[PDB]
Each structure stands twice: as structure tokens, then as C-alpha cells.
Amino acid sequence: EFLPLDERAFEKTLTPIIQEYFEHGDTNEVAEMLRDLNLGEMKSGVPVLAVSLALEGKASHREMTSKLLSDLCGTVMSTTDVEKSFDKLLKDLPELALDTPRAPQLVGQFIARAVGDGILCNTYIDSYKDCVQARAALDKATVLLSMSKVNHLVKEIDMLLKEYLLSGDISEAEHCLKELEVPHFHHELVYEAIIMVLESTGESTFKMILDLLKSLWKSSTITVDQMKRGYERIYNEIPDINLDVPHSYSVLERFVEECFQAGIISKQLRDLCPSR
């Protein structure tokens, strides 16, 4: 452990290096600067500082931090340093949550992405042993990783939806949805969401998808246009989907009717659904 004096000199020196990186994005520049600082056993403090700085910053700063961790590991910092970082990050989680209410989830994202970059191991989560917040972070990591087993936007929607089907958390799906900031492309969520409902087996996904759409409509998240666009896309492709996914029309017209009866689509949208 270190004295609060040396912890302050560390923060003071490193904050403008990290805060600047967020601005120039040059990972190599940071690498060189950290080399000249000749950090001893306080190397593991770099990912701790960078993550907590990122948490308090723009959404883009979190991705940038992940890249930084991946790049710095195996050059100026070992995997042991990185592991020690995430250990403390999970300990300081309740105090990080004070400044960033969603810290658990975002630390989950940091972990999963660290495992994906190979700077954390895939056995790190399972080998961790109080504190609900800490468990929240690990649970987010697991879900993100296991689900992870071009259309970048659709890929984000796919994962958003898959996560929602696993947890059933409307709020998490809605929040994470906005985070994407794509108001004129929510028709992509609707379309993709419906596809899952037709491809599903059992009345489980159907009911889930329906719930989500109802919630997202009432909270003014998915405007009429986006919502209408999504349905029109399905109605356009259903003669084809029918050919590959047995009884697609029957599922679709049950779904469209449920949505109309719940009052989330107009009579026009309902009526425009092909009967065949």
C-alpha cells in the first residue's frame, strides 16, 4: 500500500496524461510518457485511474480507455498489473457508484472487454469471491461475454436484445438503447426485435418482445415513425421469411394484433399486415 501523499502525486501527474489521451487518442504517446515516469508497483494504479476518469467522462472515453488498457498491457504493464487494477476497481465500486450511479454496469463492460482483448483471463470472473454492486458488475461481464460466444448499428441492437431476453430488464434495455443515440434508426430495434419473435420457439420470447415494445412506446422512446417503419419492413419480408421459418405469418398476425389491442400501433399499421 501507498501513503496518501504518493497517491496524490500519482493522480496529479497521471490525470493530465489520461485526460489528454481522451483528446488525442494516441496510445503510443501515453505509452512513452508512462515509460519515462518509471512507475514501480504503482503501475496497477494507471488502469484504476483511467477507468474512474472515464466513468466521469463522455461515453466515448470508456471505449478509448479499453483500447488504452489493451495497448499498454505487454509494453509498460503486465497482466498482473491489469488484474490488480480490476481487483481494486471492484473494491472501490460502491465509492465509484457515488459519482457514477451506473458504475457497476460500466465496470462490467470494462471487464468483458478486457477478457476479450486477452488482458484479463476468461477465468477471472468465476474465481472471484458480499457487496451487491460488485456482483452486478461481474454479472454484466458474464452476460456480455457468454452472449458474445457487418452493420455495426445492428450488432449493437442484437446484443441489446439478446441481453434483454436473458435478464428481462426493460429499464436496462431502454437506457442502453438511448446511450446509442440513434433516434431515427429505432426502426432497427423494432425490426430486429420482431425477427427474434418469429424465429423463437415457445411463447416466451413473444411475450417478452411485446412487453419491451409496449414499454418503449409509452415512454416516448420509439416514436411512431420508427415504430411504423419497423413493422413495414417485416410486412415486406414476411413472404420470404415464411419460406424459411415455419408458420411465420400466424406468429406475425398474432403479434400485430396483440400490439394493436394493447394500443401501440394504429389501425393503419394493423391493417397493412398481409393476411396471405
Image: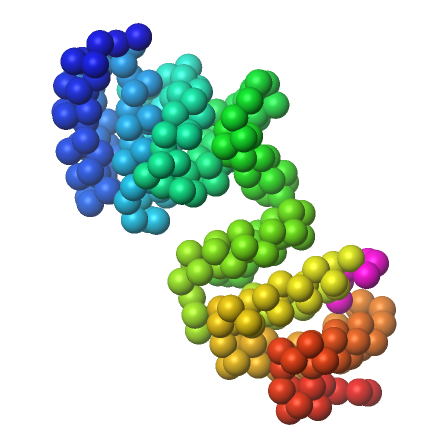
Residue 182 appearing in the image: yes
Q: Is residue 85 magenta?
A: no
Q: Residue at x 27, y 14 (%)?
A: 42
The reply, left or right, for residue 87 in relation to residue 58 is right
Which residues are drawn in magenta?
198-203
Q: Residue at x 36, y 41 (%)?
A: 100
Q: Residue at x 56, y 76 (%)?
A: 227
Residue 213: image x %, image y %? 61, 68
Q: Horizontal placement of 41 versus 262: left or right?
A: left
- The residue lying toward the viewer, choosing from 51 and 153, is 51
| Vertical side of 23 occupied by 158: above or below | below
Image position, residue 210 (x, y; %): 68, 67
**Residue 34: which quarter of the image?**
top left
In this rendered view, identify the residue nearer to me: 36 or 272.
Answer: 272
Identify whether 203 is placed above or below 118.
below
The residue drawn where x is 33% and y is 26% is 48
